[PDB]
Length: 86
Length: 14
Image (cartoon, rainbow over all chains, first blue to last red; front, side, top):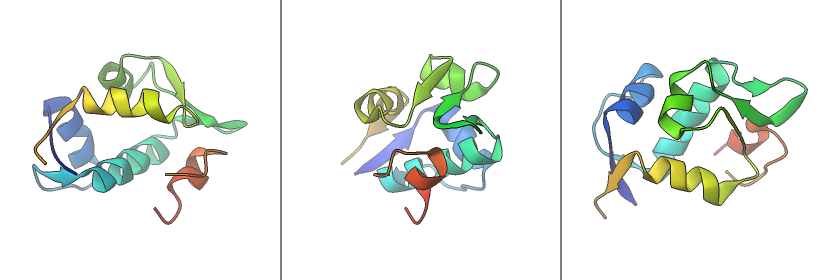
């Protein structure tokens, strides 16, 4: 699945090293993981929960926190922020 | 993107 991230998502991807405009969904998830971990956004004692109200990720996703157990919810938040091209 | 026990396990080797 090939996607074109919208400006805020693109900015977050590039902030962890990405240098292009079109990505696979695998790449988008990879870079978002790198972003979450470098920014230390997951709770050290409840590690499936991401806290993002003090981060651009929270602006992107429109939530102050989320769980990585919630796959459908996360896909929705990501898809809102890109255009799928195939 | 399949082990959801923790953010590092969800991303490791993915």
